[PDB]
Length: 314
Ligand SMILES: [Zn+2]
Ligand SMILES: [Zn+2]
Image (cartoon, rainbow, N blue to C red; front, side):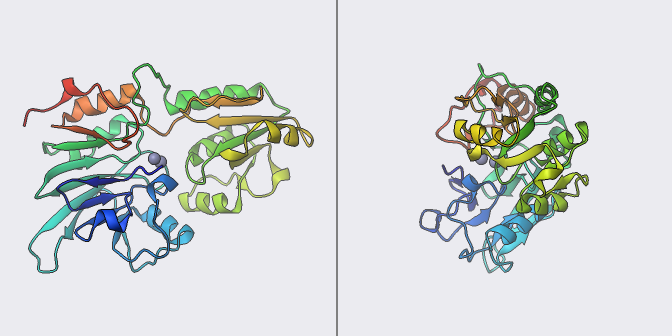
């Protein structure tokens, strides 16, 4: 899927890389390095690209986008970007920690269009309201929201509570190897927590270890499989056939940390609602505190509602 947006009546494109559809009167932004946000973005990209410093490093390393075009913006600062070559108009952009994955940010856009807050992918935490850029009384005219888990019937625990569910599960199997199905990026802090909790080395891929060292996490990761019982694998590897394959070597439990209602054939495959996306209740509190004039879903194909009673008149 493609979860990028061309914001109408603005010079803004976020996680949206189709040259034909975007046009030439746009500035391009990248919230984070998940593949559904970099569709069409590769080493051939030849336009200015604005992102976080961590995203900037990952972008050049793994997609080979030239450093000529990569524009790393410091988080928490107001950046003034030119919209033309004659110093006629500018746009002010402020990056805010999205609490989603390494490098993930929210964008605060200010310009002729007004004020727009673009969350990208984010997990709401109350500290986001205490952001200096959001405590200036500025009216947010449009709030683009991560509506991934925007289902009122879907109750999700906090990441800490979900991490506890994972810990409890692993505790029941002290003799088992543990397969954690992940994307190439994200939930590294979960791995670090599991490493310390069970005093084990967490086996990664050479790519992940390279990433972890950038984050400056604890020295608890390695590429040698014989070193630990907790293994970070690609989520696609977790299925019935691979469970039988893995059990030939050692008793194995597989864990899928996701808010998606994935069902498994194998009894030893566990799907636990550990999510990097805000829950419905967290979304409600986020919007209620900001009170924007309008709320627009980033994930168009997915449901998004229940925010009329939290909007602002202006
Ligand atoms: Zn994401
Ligand atoms: Zn996404």
